[PDB]
Amino acid sequence: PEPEQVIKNYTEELKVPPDEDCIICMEKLSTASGYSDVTDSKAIGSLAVGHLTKCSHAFHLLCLLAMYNGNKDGSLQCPSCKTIYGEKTGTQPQGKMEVLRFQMSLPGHEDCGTILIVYSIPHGIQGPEHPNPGKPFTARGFPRQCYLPDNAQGRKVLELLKVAWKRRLIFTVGTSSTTGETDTVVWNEIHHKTEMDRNITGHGYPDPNYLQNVLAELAAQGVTEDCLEQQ
Ligand SMILES: [Zn+2]
Ligand SMILES: [Zn+2]
């Protein structure tokens, strides 16, 4: 889990670095890391070069370490091909997700029924992964209802949302964009629809771009169609 440990976990030493540049610092792999002056490590020197263990893209290991300036969730993303090593997870506190389906249609989706997701997160105590470990956090507005059309795309989004939920990515502990309350349970860059009819609050359905948008948001957090498949 330690920052030097995860880089070794996802890399293999390149005995002879071929004649090429490291896309993180632009210095050739056969020469020193361009970030050696800034980044210090215990077991990684300026000349250490290695490749990621699925895509074989090569970098200075110190460059990759300086990159892993991020969440420190044990995950690492190739800057070249964006292949994700490990699994991005988040700080969603404990709670409950329930899924229902009814026949009534959402506006703009009169050809199908509706998926209803209900989330509930109780108040609690922040853990070491949270902004103020050991301090309380609050949780407003629960249970929260969210809506998806019960068509092929909405059913796919639902399956991905369940994965994001299990990865603690749906909610985080942060500052409410609406009340300014700090240390509270808020959304985490995966936008949900919380009303059926957008004309009441200005938020809801129809929204032709919504499903495409949320798939992209899920993918940016490493939740993809490939995550649904099992050998
Ligand atoms: Zn480099
Ligand atoms: Zn790669």
Image (tube, rainbow, N blue to C red):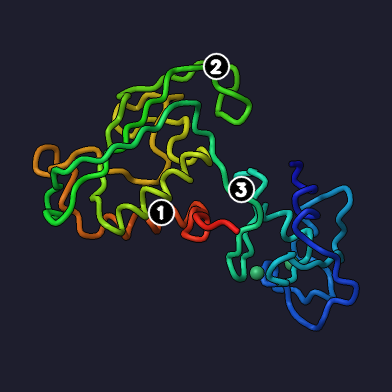
Please give the name of the residue rendered at 17% of the width and 48% of the height, measured from the top-left corner. 205
Which one is in front in this view, the residue at disc 1 or the one at disc 2?
Answer: 1
Question: Circle 3 sits in a helix, a strand or a loop, which is it?
Answer: loop
Q: Are marks 1 and 3 in contact (CB under 8 Å)?
A: no
**Gap between marks 1 and 3, in whole Å?**
18 Å
Looking at the rendering, in which quadrant would you find the C terminus?
bottom right
Looking at the rendered structure, the kind of residue marked 1 is Glu
Q: For residue 155, which numbered disc appears in the image?
A: none
Q: For residue 70, which numbered disc appears in the image?
A: 3
Q: Residues within 10 Å of mark 1 (few under 14, many from 20)?
A: some
Which one is in front in this view, the residue at disc 1 or the one at disc 3?
Answer: 1
Query: Residue 138 at what x, y percent from top left?
Result: 42, 19
Q: For residue 217, which numbered disc appears in the image?
A: 1
Please give the name of the residue rendered at 43% of the width and 35% of the height, measured from the top-left corner. 171
**Mark 2: C-beta under 8 Å from nearest atom of ligand 1:** no
Taking the image as shown, residue 162 lies to the left or right of residue 114, namely right
Q: Residues within 10 Å of mark 3 (few under 14, many from 20)?
A: few
User: From what the image shows, is residue 153 above or below residue 4?
Assistant: below
Compare residues 144 and 74 and report the one nearer the observer.
Answer: 144
Question: Circle 1 sits in a helix, a strand or a loop, which is it?
Answer: helix
Please give the name of the residue rendered at 52% of the width and 55% of the height, measured from the top-left corner. 227
Looking at the rendered structure, the kind of residue marked 3 is Gly
**Gap between marks 1 and 2, in whole Å?**
30 Å
Provide the residue designation for mark 2.
135
- Sooner in the amino-acid sequence: mark 1 or mark 3: 3
Looking at the rendered structure, the kind of residue marked 2 is Lys
User: From what the image shows, is residue 99 above or below residue 181?
Assistant: below
| Rendered-image quarter of ligand 2 | bottom right
Question: Circle 2 sits in a helix, a strand or a loop, which is it?
Answer: loop
Query: Residue 110 at what x, y percent from top left?
Result: 11, 54
Taking the image as shown, residue 56 lies to the left or right of residue 177, namely right
Taking the image as shown, residue 210 lies to the left or right of residue 136, namely left
